[PDB]
Image (cartoon, rainbow, N blue to C red):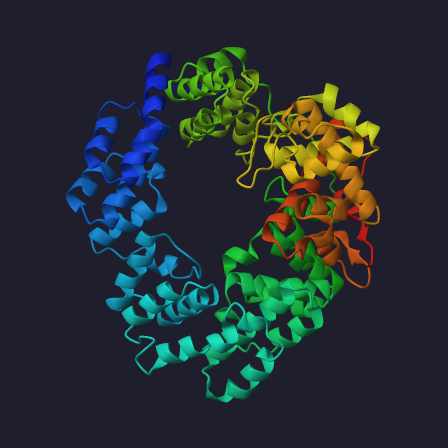
Length: 576
């Protein structure tokens, strides 16, 4: 049985929820304008909502930056700890001279929020930072064009860029490690000339920068030559070491791949990606029992691309039967009466009736707030509540957060079959692949719109819809209707596939990044499909391809199609 236990937090009338939402954008503006009296007025009678939590977090970031520590401390207490923003925590700890968070924060080599950046600078100046990690972060910031943050951290460490010591040497290395300098045909020659005067750590990082550029540019032989000159691989950033593994993977250097993975931080080693590829390396080198152990570890990581591939190496196929019963209908009803769930449903329903996309976004935030810390039984109950109300993305959001109790019909919902199936059939494309793409693109939100303007269930760009419409006799504004969106997106899947040697992996990459990019990422010889996917240079497209194809495997099982292993779906990407 699933438990019937549901929360019973105080509910507020719909009028109150809508009134609070009416003031929400103005409260965020008041934060930006430093109108503390207006922000306090908004919060004074606010419900215990994501609206209040969001405003409070943003206010606290501003209060921390302006050093209003008395008001900061008072408002910080009012956040639920799981709802405190990262930067807010950094400001809070800093104000108490508590640098506990620095040991883990300093391992980040990229941009951090201002409060956390300053926490690290303060720890550095008090001698509370590991020197190896601190200088690795300075180098990471230099290589990531965060020169001001790199400069300020080096000064806090007592070796400023203008001081003639270590900091000045790290800054001078930009002639090799700079964003454009690393691309120069002479970068490796320049680094080789100055190598003698560099420390072990400086040399290792700089070869890592050059290797990373070549690897991400898919110049695999040169990438491996440069990465081979890295004497201390733990000096590399996470991105650098993953791109070393990717080059070794693409070259099928199984021994070197296993060696690189063994130098990764443990968090990277335990990721599905590197558990699976280390297992494949062990298999390729005849270490069969160790491969099996790693495949089992990767398969236990959830419902993701590499967990599915690892299961297949163990002889396990996807099985989409639920391992729990349906939630009882009384619990599904009573879940909607909880005050925080009700608030989210109120904003969702009013976003539909009023055609208010910003209100819908806040309804999502209220849902995530309301379901935070739910156990698995409550997650599965709330997932059905969301589905019944048509809040499709939040049904998936809640169902996908379980670990043990699996409802595949709520993780892999399939609304709109009377439209999607027909359009997919009409262009001869796999309907499970189409559903897998929709799940990733829009989570079944008909009005979804990305930051760059991609529109609808299938997230087609307006510029693309204009081209499509001119080819298949449509008006470009049909992009904004569900049926026209699906017609355009399915046609574009098929057309992109035709332009890319009729390969579904290339087509998935090309849908997101353009066919020109998908073809640039090919090699002069064939690539195993999962190797192509893992070595896609664009991080967004790399994640996209793996998620779409894993989704497709789950949809195909639910749809009852003749079985296609995920490894077969990935197949072989052809040579250019």
